[PDB]
Image 1 (cartoon, rainbow, N blue to C red):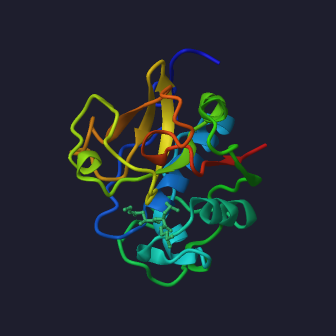
Image 2: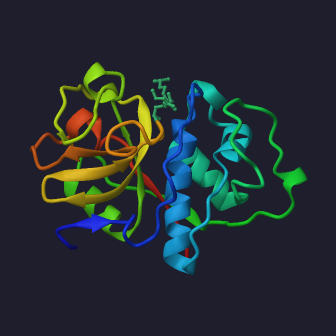
Length: 212
Ligand SMILES: *[C@@H](C(=O)OCC)[C@H](O)C(=O)N[C@@H](CC(C)C)C(=O)NCCC(C)C
């Protein structure tokens, strides 16, 4: 795999979103990976509905948080609608998939990246955007405005984001806190520290959709 990967330059990443006060990071994270893999397979970059996952993933807890892997299993089992069809409202409502007509996209499964393994994660990122978790509660992460982020942070992972690239010293992360946060909505987090948890626990729990 190459020294640099940046799915934004391959046109596989949609604009940065703001999840608002809703604890819907897990859905935003999942959708980034779906938007990425659909563009990789079909050549079309579309935006898909975080709201649908919020509303429809019964294993997750709506705005109280949830699981990227569940949301990704939902899209593999059922599918997902366009974001324009099922726009984000920032509150959990009832699952409206049936009222929104046929699904716009469907994946074929979910895979987990071997945890606590930087190389495994980089390999996955080189193939497609990956859903990753990290500890975002620390003020240093919250106040990040740019640069390669090294912490401080612990491994009390609490926030799902998407890894859309990497370089020799960092993993490139699309956050869901709007374009005002970090580097136009992105964070580069240090890699290669030999910490098997990853910086801020970044290697704890990583998943990606499979699309044939
Ligand atoms: C993420 C978010 O929108 O805000 C981050 C502060 C959610 O809070 C979320 O879904 N968190 C998620 C942790 C990873 C992403 C799976 C979660 O389920 N946290 C609660 C875990 C606890 C019950 C042990």
